[PDB]
Amino acid sequence: HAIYNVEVETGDREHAGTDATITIRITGAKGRTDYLKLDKGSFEAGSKEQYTVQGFDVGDIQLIELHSDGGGYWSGDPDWFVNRVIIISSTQDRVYSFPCFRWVIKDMVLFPGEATLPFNEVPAIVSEQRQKELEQRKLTYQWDYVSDDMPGNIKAKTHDDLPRDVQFTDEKSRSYQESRKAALVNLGIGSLFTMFENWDSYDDYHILYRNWILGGTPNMADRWHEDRWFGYQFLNGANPVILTRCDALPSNFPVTNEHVNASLDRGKNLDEEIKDGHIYIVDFKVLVGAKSYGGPVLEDIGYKVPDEADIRYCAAPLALFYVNKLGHLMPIAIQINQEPGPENPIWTPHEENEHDWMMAKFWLGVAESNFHQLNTHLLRTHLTTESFALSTWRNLASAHPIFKLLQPHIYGVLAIDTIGRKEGGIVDQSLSLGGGGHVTFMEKCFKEVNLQDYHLPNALKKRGVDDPSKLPGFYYRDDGLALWEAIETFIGEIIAIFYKNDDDVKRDNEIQSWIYDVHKNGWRVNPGHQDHGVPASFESREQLKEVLTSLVFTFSCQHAAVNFSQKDHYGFTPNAPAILRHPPPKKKGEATLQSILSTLPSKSQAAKAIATVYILTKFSEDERYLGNYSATAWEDKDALDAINRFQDKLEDISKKIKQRNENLEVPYIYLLPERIPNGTAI
Ligand SMILES: [Ca+2]
Ligand SMILES: [Ca+2]
Ligand SMILES: [Ca+2]
Ligand SMILES: [Cl-]
Ligand SMILES: [Fe+2]
């Protein structure tokens, strides 16, 4: 016989413990034990428990199987989250270490030692069990679709229908459900306080963030009305993804030197500034044809010739910006809709009537808000990356090194996206496109999505926004690029530990199925779709790196930059309205403060926008931030060294951002590693 010393580490998360009866079967080269009882004492969350069981001597241990009887009549929560099992056999001179970091329901198979690719040499019984795991994953983790024009999501009726490995922790559930209760309370309290106010100035909106715990006053509250800070936010606000270098005006945007000359300040006219690379543009054309709430449909001309019903408007503006001699991005011209003419003219900061320029900025702001929330945030982080999270569960075995790499980063997205698909939520009460056009709009955007868009260096280059001498003070870019490189370096080092060359990439059928599943069933090239840029297979380590870097960066950094920026951005509503209530003007000279206030969001619309931001930006008490791999399943020493390097590099990037920030009038904090969750979980 053999003596086996067995130590089980239980996860610290809530409900991690069990009082199920637990047994363990040990398999090795010589045979296998029966199920042996792990009998005395409790399995509490965070516990490290020791057992000595005796049984057939299996020789060199090859795998183990844990069994839970699923508890008895009184068991509150028999599911048991196991971190690791360590075993010493009295007959083998070594320590077997079995990473888990997954929920044990009834049966769990675990292998000792380092991650392997499916073709690495292992006992046949290990290979058979790997295949059984993958077969089982394909039944639990299934595709489903909002429509032919949306990226694949997880099939699940409600959150509690998700497999436990992909549900929120009980901590995240509490964080989330508690934040909805507080939103409702803060709304009701605020509604009482402001019940009989007549809103008659921009400054009345400050009341609305005042009884909310937001992390501080939105940092644009004192400056939103200055052109300089309006422009700044196209670089450093919630939507830093659409501005591009203008190398020629669009044909439908006929801004002349005479429109903007009073704004230029380096001694050159528009044509020269265009050639000098100091002219930048955003074009919201994708918003043409959008159906806003109450029924208006956006046209190239705006809206046709139409009591207080809830009717909302949006725009498809172009706007032109100029980097002035002090390095500030200045807004210099806005055309509210696509089709130039006397009814859709060009507004500049030199309007005879100052209210007309303000109103033009609000229309540009409403376009941006609906674009940002639906395309930039929801679709391009949450919904699109969700397909890859799902594929990872379907196709990558738990012993696979790239399963182990992705685990900290895919966590959360399935949970929150399933919740969201249930939670007339908001959307609906706080966005002009709420009520159903928001789905059509994301479909519209999805048809253009390409995987190459998720490549940060390439996208910035392509936009022409990557030269700090022509476009200064772009901290999303600077911090983004430093994080991208750190992530890429680390991912490259992981790959090299397990893939020794490109044939290893080609021979790995799991990584091949992983990418193929997204290509075929995830980002489906359907009728009317552009190619989505997802490869059908992998041919090289470098290609494998690029895709994993895109993906990890997007889960963590990109989602953080466009999500957690929302308090500063939307907290003071006039800085970024997401609903407007009247149609654009058809001539100059009509705007007054009063007409402007009746166009801007109402008090409850603005309050419901703040409530949404409060929910979508609440970090949970158990959040893990970028590089914090304390709940990961790695055993390989070289992999742990790579992790060490990555963490020291993030720490260096962190200090550097802090030192940059202390010389900034408005520090840029959303891409600090300690503020970037590993994943998209809210
Ligand atoms: Ca439990
Ligand atoms: Ca004990
Ligand atoms: Ca370490
Ligand atoms: Cl490993
Ligand atoms: Fe989010």
Image (cartoon, rainbow, N blue to C red):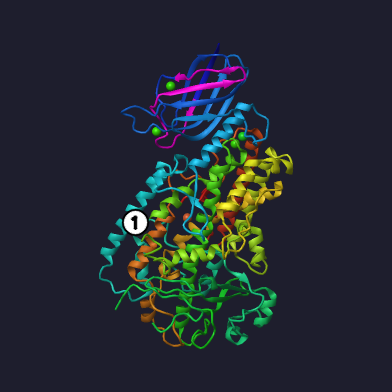
Q: Is residue 258 magenta?
A: no
Which residue corresponds to the image point at 61% horizontal and 38% vertical from the top-left?
400
Which image quarter: residue 43? top left
| Some atom of ligand 5 lies within 8 Å of the CB belonging to the residue at label 1 | no
* Three-letter code for the amino acid on which mark 1 is drawn: Ala
Q: Is residue 24 magenta?
A: yes
Name the one closer to the observer, 372 or 391.
Answer: 391
- Do we see residue 338 in this rendering? yes
Which image quarter: residue 105? top left
Q: Residue 330 location, x and y as percent?
A: 56, 74
- Residue reaching furthest front? 527
Q: Is residue 504 above or below residue 65?
A: below
Where the N terminus falls, by quadrant?
top right
Q: Please state the extent of the stretch shown in magenta in the rendering.
A: 8-37
Residue 162 vs residue 641: left or right? left
Residue 174 vs residue 376: left or right? left
- Kindly state the secondary structure of the residue where label 1 is placed: helix
Q: Residue 130 location, x and y as percent?
A: 58, 33
In the picture of the structure, the residue carrying the numbered disc 1 is 183
Residue 326 vs residue 605: left or right? right
Q: Residue 623 location, x and y as percent?
A: 47, 45
